[PDB]
Image (cartoon, helix red, strand yellow):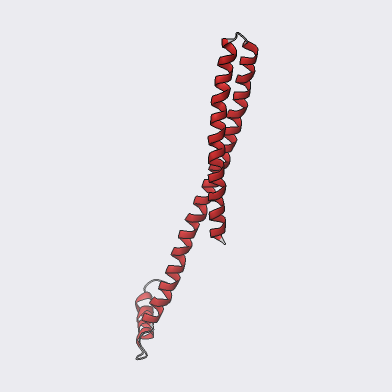
Length: 125
């Protein structure tokens, strides 16, 4: 059903947003590791922590790309649900507009109407 798909996009999105949260802390700690490495004058291990900081940032990027893909899929489902809610409402309204137009067991009117049309409409070809 559309709603099982809905709940699941939300569960996966929620999960990703704290992957996001965890990664950012990890980026913050690589930043702090490289600084401490410089305070011992080890520029190389400070450079290495910076390279590792960059890989975590790329991973974060791809975590946010997954989230966004899921959020747009979610919007499309709920937008399509509202559109279906409209169509069913119009289909039920047209049936109701038909009962009202057939609201005369008596008499004769609507095909008296339909060939007064043909006289008026006859001015066209």
